[PDB]
Length: 7
Length: 18
Length: 298
Image (tube, rainbow over all chains, first blue to last red; front, side, top):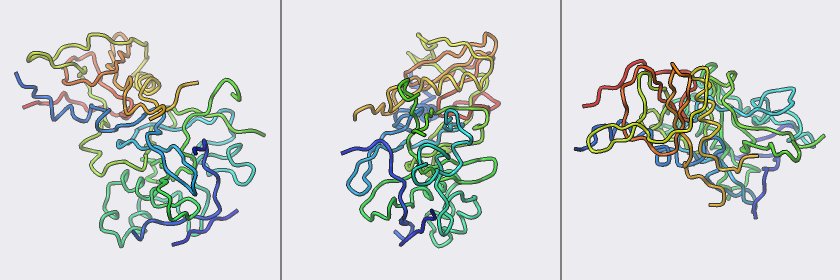
């Protein structure tokens, strides 16, 4: 599980 | 309604840009 | 006469300057996708505070375990992200916030608090939820805490949810527990160092009087007295505005170094008494650092 960041 | 523990989410945002 | 200690003692009025629990800080509520959560909201940093996870392979600064292992294994810290948000050294935070004049030059503790506060759970654009953080003052690293809970140690449950409690452990001496509300000016308005050759008192008719009623607990050294004050301090959770302490509790101690007595009390002190046998401490204060000289009050 790898988590992305969004704007 | 309240919950005891926050779920482990898959995605996150950033407030940094106001 | 008028009290000359007023300005000096302002940082010791814990209910006013911190305004939340110390041992368990859950002074506010926030929302994530329609659901309400309790979260830390103290305005002061808590020096030496960490979370002990009962019967654990790791420490609380280890990232949270994933999937069905979440809350069973791992620690409390933010899991790895793309790009990596936690842990973040002081230098990396200042570089990351280089375009923001209001954040890039904040003191390290405030910066770690603001950095943790930038993470939106589930990218819910309506969420006011702000993760707390732990700053390691030795390695200069900010650890965003994914888990805002501080105590789960009911005789009931304590493969399943882990059991844990807050504590000032010797291994946490350089850690600083930070809510989303940690103030920019903490150094001037919050306690940090313990006061050597000083005893807290109460200003009455032009004289600094002794605290008239204290709760005496034995302690081998200052660190153990600070652990005791922390254990009995303001708590937003019943031990094992609903359960909100608002900063009210046994947050102050006068440590007698000679009799090895930690004299714990629950009212705000309004002056200091110069006494060679004493060290004045608070639940918020560093468990080891001492300010060597008694203050000169004008």
